[PDB]
Amino acid sequence: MDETGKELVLALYDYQEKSPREVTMKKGDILTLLNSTNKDWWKVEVKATANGKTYERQGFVPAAYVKKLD
């Protein structure tokens, strides 16, 4: 698994993606931080299981609900 070993953020409040170019999280969840160039939204990589395979996808999350564990 080469999708966990750089940065991660903790999810304070649950979320609910609305677009295909976005992700979601749950209270007490952890997402691998990818980019934080912004101050309102952060780019994290989530995981998903389909067709009997595990793959990760990129998305954006509210920095107001999530906080890096740096």
Image (tube, helix red, strand yellow):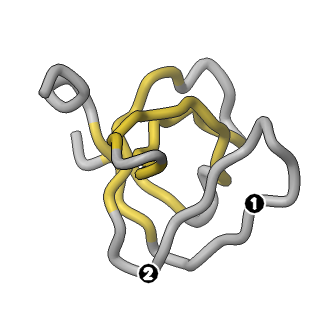
Mark 1: which amino acid?
Answer: Glu
Looking at the picture, how far across and down is residue 29, in whole percent? 35, 68
Residue 58: image tag: none
At x 35%, y 48%, the residue is: 52
The mark closer to the camera, 1 or 2, is 1
Looking at the picture, how far across and down is residue 18, in whole percent? 86, 59
Q: Are marks 1 and 2 in contact (CB under 8 Å)?
A: no
At x 13%, y 28%, the residue is: 1
The answer to which of marks 1 and 2 sits earlier in the sequence is 1
Looking at the picture, how far across and down is residue 44, in whole percent? 50, 36
Q: Which of 69 and 31 is in front in this view?
A: 31
Mark 2: which amino acid?
Answer: Lys
Query: What is the crowding at mark 2: few (fewer than 14 residues within 10 Å), some, or many (at least 20)?
Result: few
Please, is residue 67 above or below residue 39 in the view? Answer: below
Please, is residue 37 above or below residue 13 in the view? Answer: above
Q: Mark 1 points at which residue?
A: 17
Q: Mark 2 points at which residue?
A: 27
Q: Nearer the viewer, residue 47 or 27?
A: 47
